[PDB]
Image (cartoon, coloured by chain):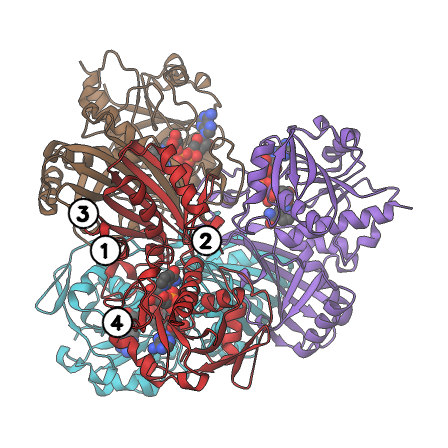
Chain colours: A red, B cyan, C purple, D brown
Amino acid sequence: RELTVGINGFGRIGRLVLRACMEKGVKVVAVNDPFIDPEYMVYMFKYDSTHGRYKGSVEFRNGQLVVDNHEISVYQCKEPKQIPWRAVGSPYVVESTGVYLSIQAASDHISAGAQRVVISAPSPDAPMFVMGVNENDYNPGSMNIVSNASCTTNCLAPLAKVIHERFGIVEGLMTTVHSYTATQKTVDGPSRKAWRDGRGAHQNIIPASTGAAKAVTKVIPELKGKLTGMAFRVPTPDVSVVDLTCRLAQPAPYSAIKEAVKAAAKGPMAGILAYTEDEVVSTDFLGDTHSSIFDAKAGIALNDNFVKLISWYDNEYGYSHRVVDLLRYMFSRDAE
Amino acid sequence: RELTVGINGFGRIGRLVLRACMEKGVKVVAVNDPFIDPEYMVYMFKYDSTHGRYKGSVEFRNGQLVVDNHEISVYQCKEPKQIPWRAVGSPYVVESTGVYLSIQAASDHISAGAQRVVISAPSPDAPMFVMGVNENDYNPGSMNIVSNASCTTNCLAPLAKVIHERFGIVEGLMTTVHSYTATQKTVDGPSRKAWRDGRGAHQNIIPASTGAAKAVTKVIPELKGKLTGMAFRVPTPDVSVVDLTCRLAQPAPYSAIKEAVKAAAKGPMAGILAYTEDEVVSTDFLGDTHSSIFDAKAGIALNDNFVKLISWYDNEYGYSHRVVDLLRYMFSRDAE
Amino acid sequence: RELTVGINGFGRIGRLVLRACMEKGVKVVAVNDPFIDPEYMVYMFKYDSTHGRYKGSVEFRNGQLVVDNHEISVYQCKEPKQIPWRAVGSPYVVESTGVYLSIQAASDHISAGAQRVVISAPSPDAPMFVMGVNENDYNPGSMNIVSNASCTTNCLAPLAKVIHERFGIVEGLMTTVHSYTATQKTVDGPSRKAWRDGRGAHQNIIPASTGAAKAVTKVIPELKGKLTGMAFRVPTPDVSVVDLTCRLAQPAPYSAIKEAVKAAAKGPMAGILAYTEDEVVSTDFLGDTHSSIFDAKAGIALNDNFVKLISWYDNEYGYSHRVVDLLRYMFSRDAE
Amino acid sequence: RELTVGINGFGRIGRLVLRACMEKGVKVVAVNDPFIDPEYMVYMFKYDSTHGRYKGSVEFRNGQLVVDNHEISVYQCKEPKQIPWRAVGSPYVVESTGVYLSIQAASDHISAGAQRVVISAPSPDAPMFVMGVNENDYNPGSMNIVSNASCTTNCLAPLAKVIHERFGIVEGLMTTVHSYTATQKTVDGPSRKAWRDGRGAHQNIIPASTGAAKAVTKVIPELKGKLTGMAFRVPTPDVSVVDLTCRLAQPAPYSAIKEAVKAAAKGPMAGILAYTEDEVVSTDFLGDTHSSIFDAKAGIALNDNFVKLISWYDNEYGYSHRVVDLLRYMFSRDAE
Ligand SMILES: NC(=O)c1ccc[n+]([C@@H]2O[C@H](COP(=O)([O-])OP(=O)(O)OC[C@H]3O[C@@H](n4cnc5c(N)ncnc54)[C@H](O)[C@@H]3O)[C@@H](O)[C@H]2O)c1
Ligand SMILES: NC(=O)c1ccc[n+]([C@@H]2O[C@H](COP(=O)([O-])OP(=O)(O)OC[C@H]3O[C@@H](n4cnc5c(N)ncnc54)[C@H](O)[C@@H]3O)[C@@H](O)[C@H]2O)c1
Ligand SMILES: NC(=O)c1ccc[n+]([C@@H]2O[C@H](COP(=O)([O-])OP(=O)(O)OC[C@H]3O[C@@H](n4cnc5c(N)ncnc54)[C@H](O)[C@@H]3O)[C@@H](O)[C@H]2O)c1
Ligand SMILES: NC(=O)c1ccc[n+]([C@@H]2O[C@H](COP(=O)([O-])OP(=O)(O)OC[C@H]3O[C@@H](n4cnc5c(N)ncnc54)[C@H](O)[C@@H]3O)[C@@H](O)[C@H]2O)c1
């Protein structure tokens, strides 16, 4: 009858997914987090260092979180298999813990009663979707567990689609200058799997690997072999920027690039890709719901066939809105 | 024969304790950390965001850390009881994990072969020592497990001793404006035991409780009932400041306060308490080995009996040196 | 007929005063800033690193700034005497440049045609007002040029008034942990008048003098001789906190302190002083319009007569609102 | 007889140039800064937020700065033409104010008695030099006034020279993720010439233009038309990184790129270009004297002909050393 949602992991993305759901009239029926009891959830949801106080009412009673009079069951389970999704009637589950990334790890939600799962991160094997790029690849009958890619991939893929369809990308290399996140440390500490990520996040420009540019070639297969990249983590709490250096097949004077991006923004990618010529900086995108905001004046061309294109994203807020848009899209299609 | 040391928990304090030991010719024979293998220890020890590259040679071989040609056994045990302290011959153990604070929790080191333990933090029950204040209270025959207090207590106690002995402290209230630490978060996340400490460390002035001012009254009993305080955590990676507002028994014109602090610095507290009149700010104390640096010009008096006194400390580096000074003192006394 | 306002110096305060004036329906008829032409004023007004995009329309035409269809004359004069206030019909002028602080310096606005001047900072000699504390001391016939004090004074004075009137303040010493401002530097540079204020704002805890605590004894003369204080500047862009350590005449158990503050907040100081028991940190007060937000749980008492009281303020936003409230009050009273 | 130096503008570069000169035994005979009297110069020189306390003695007497017993005349002139260079016997002048960039502007030093001028920034017209790249283009008889380029150019040019000479650069596009500097603001303020640079430095990723990548094609003319780039300013106080995305003529497997860079570092560019494979972040280069430190593991290749190369630089310290190396080179050659 209606889209109902459950959120596993009430972190940055989990909480801002809940905000996005409220803004978009999507029913959340449960939140599970083992480290956050209902009264503490109220606090964490209401006050936000980056995105301000929640505009609305937040309370708890009866082991529930109450947002603007909508009651939300709260569970405290450490593993997906333990979560009582059947109790709240087979909701679509957002898997936002960061620790259950494979189809196998995620499927424990399905066996615990979830109708679908959207992993809020890239998956080694779940099929991957970027709204505005390949969401039509979703198959209601055969895809119980999907991935909504990364924030970075949601920024690059829409831009890469427009540039590729208009000019042809021969080859590209991406850098994202990216805000620090929850996986990083306040001071130099242990990160055995990626030593540089242990270094103090507030003190350092930190190079990091990312699969996000390659991930674009999974959602736009015709770019296979033509894109990769890396990241720098820097001392800002939110908002990131993509810097795509690409070699183009057809002549691409910069005025022609701008006309293509503007047309995409105003039409087939309205709400996903935005276009600006203002003299913006990162804080200007706090709370912006777009996946990718093309910065006309920040980019530079060496010539008509070799350009550096710049596009912003609120990696927390934009991505969280895409999770909700993907959920809603899945549901309309699952009515087939 | 000689002081030998083992370090449990190769974090900020563990690593800077090792630096301090090298600077002071103290033999470290083992480091245990379950999350840091020998080759990774080399990296973590050599490069430091706050205190620069280690000036010397750092390498590994044979499952050992080699600092300036001194070989250090590396263990990888998750619990004190598992650590083979007997293997390296009953060393004095620095317990710097932050998780083994009681006499009971710490004593597992003794049963695993440690001669003594210095907990690098306040303890609910271990006796507590501040070099320059009460280290003579140490009893070789009856104190296997001690605490070296907190960084803040090592800053306040020496100042409080001088002011109290010269003027009489009727009552005092302390604020420490304190750098963020490893227990804090890069972005708003879970801190169930102290909700405010979960809020993004780089973004916020964060009020926090601290027992450090009261802890001064344990190491200077005559101040019992006369001191307490609180903290603000702020967006700096190291160096903190004590702001002691006190009501004094005898007239204390500020010139008289300065003469007392200077005399203590030049004599009975040389190396522990320092005195400055320069126009300093926090970065000026990076790497400073003193427990407490009195800032003459930052303080203000309402009158001769009510004053606000300001004193700095490198909470990482100064404290780490005091751990080493306490170890060395214990050892000279344990020869009795 | 109506309150009309001119702003001299379209900086942090100047711009946020315009925001406050729009929010409160107060007519701004001109802005003067020699370093900001109208088109640039649109940009600076529209986008704000700390307080988000202006919610409304911002444009320029005909050498005017147009905010939500209200047209604002823009002047570009380097000195008050040069500004054509007569042209926009004798407005009340906000003097927010930071450089015209005395009666003598500010009186050039009056001779250039301003009806009144409110200096957005303490003055060596203009009379000083804190809304909710002493605004009734304003005399329409004899005070052309007034001061609205500092952000810090506006935070401390209302709290001090409540505490003094209920319990009696014997003596007090204040610290404010304060966000950096426009007078500070990005990296170590020249500050000949106050050397510490030249040191990098983002890197340091910086001790600073402030007359703000003494200024409270100007606006509450019964506190003369009983209050002073100092400041620490820290690496946050906005929001500050007052820490008042005070000896009280009547017993003041903390529960009684809280009832006094809550009753003031609900009644005679509604909108000026607020009361909270939530686990707040500084970002929680971004955009808060109160002069003072008492933090119940952050404060600490040594005993019933010696307490540390903690109160927050958005130094930029709250203060800017008080400028507008003072303008509006001056005008209703100037109708006499 | 000997190289003697005068510094105009005792800022970040000016002060660190004096540090470099002490480290390298180069005689500084005068410093001019109108905003810094001798006693204040002691303070600014002695204490440094980013590079620690000066290791040595710093004092003033007789209107002189005394660093390690070397006496330095201090002048206080607002314009080059006013400075008494003749009084200290025709020194080589470092022009580090940021405001006298042209041949015409800088030539007032020559007529005020300077033997040579090195402008510590790019010039619209002075010839430009990068040590290790084109210093041999200097002509003692015809070049009174030269430029030492920018920090960024000094990082990119040596790397570009190596890569171009080994593999051929077809085309390249550079991004530098760059620490904030003295021209930026603590909070959103006026930057009429470049609006984005006015936005709060500590809060934002800020896109900026830079001529630095083009400037490399001035110092390596064979790259004309083949290189340009842009910048992001980010919230770190010092140390920056170059990200060069380039198409190469000959196949360049990454292993071959690394051997070329290592062989340059060990040989013809010893001291200018360094090579690392450690897991470094920006603070790891504080105080590093190299112009360029190639980060082997941070770079990424799409294929053998399309690569992203990553190289670090302490924009303050490394560049300052190059000023001193250029002075010393100019002098040995001026003996002709
Ligand atoms: N923050 C961003 O910019 C962003 C953007 C896109 C994708 N992502 C991805 O979203 C996922 C979550 O990221 P985040 O930034 O919200 O991290 P976070 O640390 O803020 O979120 C983790 C939350 O999940 C909880 N949790 C941990 N283990 C759990 C378990 N076993 N069961 C239930 N809950 C558990 C934690 O309490 C925490 O509240 C990660 O894969 C991350 O890569 C993050
Ligand atoms: N950093 C300071 O300013 C400071 C000052 C005084 C006291 N302290 C105290 O020192 C203690 C350590 O603080 P820190 O700042 O070094 O924290 P940290 O996070 O830097 O140190 C923790 C280290 O111990 C390791 N560890 C965790 N659990 C372990 C276990 N079970 N067995 C062995 N090792 C384990 C972690 O890998 C980490 O390397 C804490 O009690 C802290 O309160 C810190
Ligand atoms: N920011 C705060 O937290 C705060 C709070 C309370 C009071 N104040 C006071 O408000 C005053 C302004 O503060 P701010 O933070 O907005 O500073 P700011 O530097 O942000 O604003 C100053 C503005 O004045 C302009 N200006 C400079 N000289 C001028 C002149 N001669 N004529 C006209 N305009 C000129 C500049 O262009 C700039 O836009 C200062 O006295 C400050 O002490 C600031
Ligand atoms: N900081 C870096 O990373 C860096 C690197 C390479 C080049 N540069 C260039 O070096 C030059 C100086 O840079 P900075 O970062 O040291 O700036 P800064 O602002 O730190 O130093 C400028 C100094 O010049 C002084 N000054 C101003 N006007 C003067 C005048 N008329 N006469 C004499 N002194 C005057 C100021 O008092 C200040 O001490 C600029 O051109 C800058 O582009 C900077």
Q: Tell me whether the residue at label 4 lies in contact with that at label 1, contact meaning CB atoms closer than 8 angstroms.
A: no
- Name the residue carrying label 4: A102
- Name the residue carrying label 3: D302
Q: CA–CA distance between discs 4 and 1? A: 41 Å
Dot 2 and dot 4 within a common chain: yes
Q: Tell me whether the residue at label 1 lies in contact with that at label 3, contact meaning CB atoms closer than 8 angstroms.
A: no
Where in the figure is residue B213, as x and y percent of width and height?
A: 50, 72
Q: Chain of mark 3?
A: D
Dot 3 and dot 4 within a common chain: no
Q: CA–CA distance between discs 2 and 4? A: 29 Å
Give the amino acid at mark 4: Ser
Badge 1 residue CB within 8 Å of ligand 2: no
- Name the residue carrying label 1: B54
Viewer-side label of 4, 1: 4
Mark 4 nearby-residue class (10 Å; few <14, some 14–19, many ≥20): some
Q: Residue at x 40, y 72 (%)?
A: A335
Q: Is residue D65 left or right of residue A103?
A: right
Q: Residue at x 72, y 61 (%)?
A: C271
Q: Which mark is residue A271?
A: 2
Q: Is residue C274 above or below residue A105?
A: above
Q: Residue at x 15, y 82 (%)?
A: B86
Q: Tell me whether the residue at label 1 lies in contact with that at label 2, contact meaning CB atoms closer than 8 angstroms.
A: no
